Length: 111
Image 1: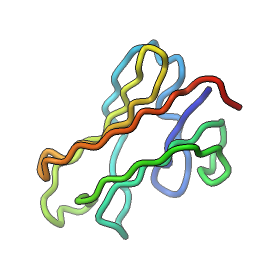
Image 2: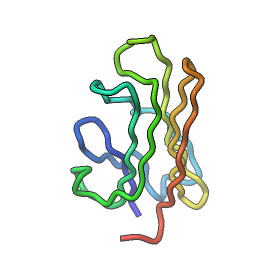
Image 3: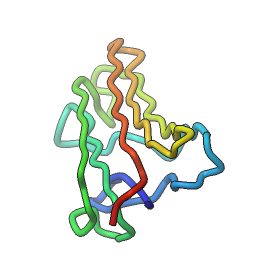
């Protein structure tokens, strides 16, 4: 099923779909939004629905040492990797901090 993430403004965006010509590897329109934190917080939202809070979460993952502003001149890119089965392998990698942390969520058999 459709699976978007929580993007800036407490809102879901289907930035990648079940049938994104799988498998594939998208690496754009993905940035850390959390001014009020120093971390990234992906929430994984099954369902088609604008608001993130109104859409079926079953998944989330976090990684600390991050900012939108160059508070410590970070280096962060978050990837949308879609697997053959259509699993969303959602991955944040800090090249500056040397952190990697990544999360795998199916996008099938659900409602």
